[PDB]
Amino acid sequence: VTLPPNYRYGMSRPGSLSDKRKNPPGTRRRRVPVEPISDEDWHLFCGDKVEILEGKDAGKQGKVVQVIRQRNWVVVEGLNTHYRYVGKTVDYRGTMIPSEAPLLHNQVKLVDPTDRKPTDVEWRFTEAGERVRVSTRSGRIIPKPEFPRADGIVPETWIDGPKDTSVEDALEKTYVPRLKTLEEEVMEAMGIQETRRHKKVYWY
Amino acid sequence: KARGNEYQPSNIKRKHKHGWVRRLRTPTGVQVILRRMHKGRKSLSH
Amino acid sequence: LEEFFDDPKNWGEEKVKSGASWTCQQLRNKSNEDLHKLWYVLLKERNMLLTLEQEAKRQRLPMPSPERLEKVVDSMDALDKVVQEREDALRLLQTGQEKARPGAWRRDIFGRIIWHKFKQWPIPWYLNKKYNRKRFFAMPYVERFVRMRIEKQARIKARKRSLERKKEKFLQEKFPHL
Amino acid sequence: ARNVLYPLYQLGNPQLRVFRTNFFIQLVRPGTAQPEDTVQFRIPMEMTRVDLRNYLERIYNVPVAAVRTRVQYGSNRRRDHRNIRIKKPDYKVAYVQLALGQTFTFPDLFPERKGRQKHSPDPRRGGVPGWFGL
Amino acid sequence: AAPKNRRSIEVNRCRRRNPQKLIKVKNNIDVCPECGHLKQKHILCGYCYEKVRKETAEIRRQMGKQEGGPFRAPTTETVVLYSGETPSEQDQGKRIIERERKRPSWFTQN
RNA sequence: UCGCACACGCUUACAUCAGUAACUAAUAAUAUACUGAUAAUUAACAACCAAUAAACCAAAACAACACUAAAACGUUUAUUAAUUACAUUGUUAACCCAACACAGGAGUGCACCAAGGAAAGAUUAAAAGAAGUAAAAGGAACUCGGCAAACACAAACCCCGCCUG
RNA sequence: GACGAGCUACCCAUGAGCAGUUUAAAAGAACCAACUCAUCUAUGUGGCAAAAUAGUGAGAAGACUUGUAGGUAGAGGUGAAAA
RNA sequence: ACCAAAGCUAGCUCAACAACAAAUACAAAAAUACACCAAAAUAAAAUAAAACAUUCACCUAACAUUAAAGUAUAGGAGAUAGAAAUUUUUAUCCUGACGCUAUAGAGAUAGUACCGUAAGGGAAAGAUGAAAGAAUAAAAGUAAAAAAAAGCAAA
Ligand SMILES: [Mg+2]
Ligand SMILES: [Mg+2]
Ligand SMILES: [Mg+2]
Ligand SMILES: [Mg+2]
Ligand SMILES: [Mg+2]
Ligand SMILES: [Mg+2]
Ligand SMILES: [Mg+2]
Ligand SMILES: [Mg+2]
Ligand SMILES: [Mg+2]
Ligand SMILES: [Mg+2]
Ligand SMILES: [Mg+2]
Ligand SMILES: [Mg+2]
Ligand SMILES: [Mg+2]
Ligand SMILES: [Mg+2]
Ligand SMILES: [Mg+2]
Ligand SMILES: [Mg+2]
Ligand SMILES: [Mg+2]
Ligand SMILES: [Mg+2]
Ligand SMILES: [Mg+2]
Ligand SMILES: [Mg+2]
Ligand SMILES: [Mg+2]
Ligand SMILES: [Mg+2]
Ligand SMILES: [Mg+2]
Ligand SMILES: [Mg+2]
Ligand SMILES: [Mg+2]
Ligand SMILES: [Mg+2]
Ligand SMILES: [Mg+2]
Ligand SMILES: [Mg+2]
Ligand SMILES: [Mg+2]
Ligand SMILES: [Mg+2]
Ligand SMILES: [Mg+2]
Ligand SMILES: [Mg+2]
Ligand SMILES: [Mg+2]
Ligand SMILES: [Mg+2]
Ligand SMILES: [Mg+2]
Ligand SMILES: [Mg+2]
Ligand SMILES: [Mg+2]
Ligand SMILES: [Mg+2]
Ligand SMILES: [Mg+2]
Ligand SMILES: [Zn+2]
């Protein structure tokens, strides 16, 4: 991870081509004011259903792709949209793609699953000690959007190659809590017998 | 005759006159280091 | 010597899958010999990855599944953590000296306070030449300089505060909260 | 092993041992033509000859006859936008030669095995936007 | 001597817009009957001289191949041939260069 | 026709492939000097590499033997010296000190070419300038002075310092 | 109060050069190269160069030139005195 | 029409309150052999006195605050320097700004480039947008648009 003191996040990954093009090595731009939201006060996640209250497209419903916490943005899939070409060569302009335009978190409310309405989500700690999101308006428990992971490896469908360790072996507890260190342990195990000892040494 | 070539590079003379050890041997050398740290120089001593 | 290379059938393929890197908890359960062995299974894989790295750089071709190199690092890094604990715990339980290498607190020439790591010499300290002309103490004039950085530091701290102050105000006048 | 303290040797001390070795090797395709008996390894800076020999023999079971080493100097000359120098790291290179008459060759690591729109404007249309039919 | 005063832009416009410092319009430009490119009346056509030059270069290469070394050069007259041609008796007893391209229209048989 | 090595000193400027619209070259072409990617100098040469006692008046100079100015440099005997494959490090260059890709400053060993290099971007043949060549008759008449230049290169007299420095 | 003897002045170490020709001679002798100086003239004067280039000159086994490394520091040093 | 021009932020002022690990003094960044360590002597002058010799506040210390008082005194009795005895003082809490916006405010985007053998000196700069995982035409100088007897350039 490479970051400068003044940096603008352009939907582009910090370590990427589009980003090195966006803000080259020598740029310093105006400050971007970010209304502070502490991590614990943050009520949004990627994958949950939200309602957009703002803009040309409002009152609609949508799923969240990813949240960028630095500049405080949420991403609704194919909802707020502007048009960007992909391939452009001299004689040809190919692949016109509808692209998601970023949305501020003031324009987006979290939708409670049952009656499908926008609400203010507030953190509650239950009697059992779980952290749940309770609707102020509707008075419900709001789930958080169990979602895939970045690598696209689903644990349920998986196969070991030659170099993958089978679960049974990796879990097996072989540890024998005795007072030796790795040196004396291995040396005793390998059957390497040492007799002569170190002469006295001074430390300055 | 023609001048301005006065500096004839030598690595031994350079370290012997301006090098870290030479500084540290004498009190005033030490203060050269000290002042140079107070100004926060990238290079303290030759 | 083939061990510097991937299984021959695996060369031209774009993506190659591998597992998760070892998490400490999985390593705590292994005995000493097992960690000691795992170390080399990790080592060889690391060399093979490294070689593929360089080679891919030379052939002007992007390198297949870079994730691997990240993973084999972590596990090794993990493995270390596990053994370091088992030493550092045990040495407490035996001696009660927290730090593994001998060491002292010194006032060096420049009046800083420093952690002096000891060294191992064949002869006593009063008989060692180099160790004798190393001075640990300060002189009178250093007292002045000692002051200056205390003063200099005090400014960088004092005017960092005054930045965090301003930041709070702008935001509050820019965002009429509540 | 790199970055570790070593015990000071005096007369009749225990044979020095390192249980988890700290070094790491790269096997690199030679930049110039060298005999069939030669392999080339970038090693870490602090590694001695004898170390590379034992390391190769015991980890990989290679019968090594001869080792030689040199130190490569990385350029100090490329400049940042701030006009401060970027230094490419210095690195040690070793040449090893195999004892039993074995011939090495560097494996080709990239076998090449893998897994038409013309919209061009009409010359006789004279710039008329063809989508529109009439 | 150092100039006594900055000159005004007026004086400079006078001096360097003079009808003498202006580039004259060349009136001798024509077109070449073959390739229809532009050429000056007294000068060879550039584009024609090009294809002539290229062909001369290639024929000199092949006649460099017909010669063994740097100092060795023929005592006979040379005659160059193209695909499909056989030597006349006038031209026999001479060194012959054989070429793939069928004889170019501008180069005659004679 | 200041050539190839080493010492000192510079630090990748060196090598291969690729690109040069524009940056470096005081212009272009193309590239040892710009840009990117990749590589690279391998130790037998060189650096690092014991002490203490005792004998020993007797120059280098082609060294016979001397000269005055009196000359750099170690053998051998004794007492102990870890004894054990492979230590570590320098190895490119068209280069360095002069603000410059400076008609300049730079130690040593062998060389006079076997090695290195181009004095002219294209014309035109004005003046005035710079450098060189030749000149009828005259030969210092020039000028502060025979300064400069000569197909000359020699003599004599003074003043002041004695002399080489 | 610091920092400067990598230039230059003078020393102290440790190295290195000096071909030929003449003379019984290495004799602060001749002649003349390398090497060292800087006489005289012309170019140059924001130069090729913050002191050069071309010719022409002096010395050239010595109070000779020169390499590496030390030393003396401003109320001072060093000086075959030119303040 | 070129060259240019405009933003408001980075940060500053002033004031209250009170990443290890290894490597390092060998010629710093070099694991490793016989030593030595370590040291101290008033501040001077520039300047005031219209010159300058005695003398010249502040420059070290803390002592603060309201007074006694610019008084007693000390001074080429000049310039100027200058006390004390004795008196006064209610708590914290309560932070900010008739302080600067990129020739300002820190030297600072930096003690960095670069300049110095060395102590040491010491810069310049940023600007579109919600999103680039969407592509005003106003300084001088010039161009559009050479110049026609005459003369502080105008009236
Ligand atoms: Mg200079
Ligand atoms: Mg080595
Ligand atoms: Mg080597
Ligand atoms: Mg060298
Ligand atoms: Mg150019
Ligand atoms: Mg060296
Ligand atoms: Mg060297
Ligand atoms: Mg070389
Ligand atoms: Mg110069
Ligand atoms: Mg010319
Ligand atoms: Mg003329
Ligand atoms: Mg003439
Ligand atoms: Mg003549
Ligand atoms: Mg005549
Ligand atoms: Mg006369
Ligand atoms: Mg006359
Ligand atoms: Mg006369
Ligand atoms: Mg004359
Ligand atoms: Mg007279
Ligand atoms: Mg005389
Ligand atoms: Mg003489
Ligand atoms: Mg010295
Ligand atoms: Mg000297
Ligand atoms: Mg001689
Ligand atoms: Mg003589
Ligand atoms: Mg002449
Ligand atoms: Mg002479
Ligand atoms: Mg003479
Ligand atoms: Mg003298
Ligand atoms: Mg005198
Ligand atoms: Mg005088
Ligand atoms: Mg006065
Ligand atoms: Mg006055
Ligand atoms: Mg006066
Ligand atoms: Mg005073
Ligand atoms: Mg500023
Ligand atoms: Mg420098
Ligand atoms: Mg204008
Ligand atoms: Mg008028
Ligand atoms: Zn033509």
Image (cartoon, coloured by chain):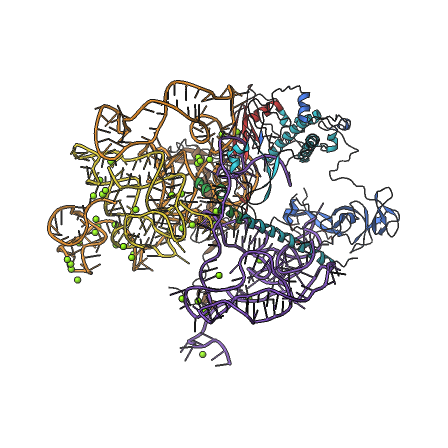
Chain colours: A blue, B green, C cyan, D red, E brown, F orange, G yellow, H purple
**Going 69% across and 53% down the picture, which residue do you hit?**
D129
Residue A89 placement (x, y as % from top left): 64, 46
Relative horizontal placement of residue G61, taking residue C62 as reference (left or right)? left
Q: Nearer the viewer, residue H122 or E106?
A: H122
H14 in relation to C31, above or below: below
Up the image or down, H32 lies above or below F120; here it is above
Count the marks: 0
Left or right, C37 with reference to F107: right
Q: Position of residue D81 (x, y in %)?
A: 57, 48
The one nearer the camera, E44 or B25, is B25
Residue A112 position within the rendered picture, expressed as x and y whole percent measured from the top left: 85, 48
- Left or right: D41 as drawn, with respect to A44: left
Q: Quadrant of the C terminus of chain A?
A: top right
Say if F52 sits above or below E108 in the image.
above
Q: Against F58, is F136 above or below? A: below
The image position of residue E49, as x and y in percent, is: 46, 46
Q: Quadrant of residue H104?
A: bottom right
Q: Give the quadrant of residue G27.
A: top left
Q: Residue at x 43, y 34 (%)?
A: E64
Compare residues D126 and C18 and report the one nearer the observer. Answer: C18
Please give left or right for residue C154 compared with residue A178 in the image: left
Q: In the rendered view of the protein, which quadrant contains the N terminus of chain A? A: top right
Whether residue E107 appears in this view of the structure is no
User: Residue at 79% of width from left, 41% of height from top?
Assistant: A147
The answer to whether residue A203 is seen in the rendering is yes
**Ligand 12 position by quadrant:** bottom left
Depth check: H34 or F122 in front? H34
